[PDB]
Length: 245
Ligand SMILES: N=C(N)c1ccc2cc([C@@H]3C[C@H]3c3ccccc3)ccc2c1
Image (cartoon, rainbow, N blue to C red; front, top):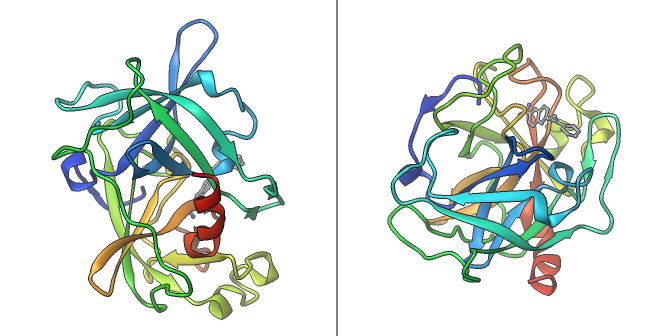
């Protein structure tokens, strides 16, 4: 997250931090995700497509720092890794960028809801918030494009939704962004999500309840003029999420 504010997990209880075990023992941070139900976490397919082995992934819930064991955290492995069978990647855009991870602890159980570990609700059919709505994003991603390390403490920020037609303008993303994706950004282009934040939650308060409206997917640079962050529009995939869970 470029700009924004440092935060802690109690402020984002459904945020999942996903790592990957490398041959040798070293572990590096991969992407974020969100808790859908006690046994399921949803993220982005592009975060796993090149290393599809479910055994190498480690998932944490209730974790506040990149290299610290936050009191109350729970560690899990991936029982089933489901990727969208129609996923593809072009020069900038990613298609059907959505994935499902069934989690299980070493004892064989799913997550246990607590003050720092909670699920987020899915959106409903044909009911997404209007352009201009402020929503929040969270992640352990880069604070600047030139940084090679990720911040040690979790961060979050607020950006606003941009209409499909505004996002299809020539200086934005033209026909590269489709009706199955959502754009969001800062009018002053000072804050935004960035590499490292992929797969994380775009949460919008809609008609009262906080909803998982989007999944951090792609974007040209980070916090650049006329180049909004692009997100997978969860409402379109409800039928897919239902059949695969
Ligand atoms: N403007 C933003 N809000 C934004 C959001 C997500 C982003 C994800 C990547 C990570 C690297 C992309 C990638 C491409 C292919 C496969 C792996 C990773 C790069 C830039 C990004 C910018």
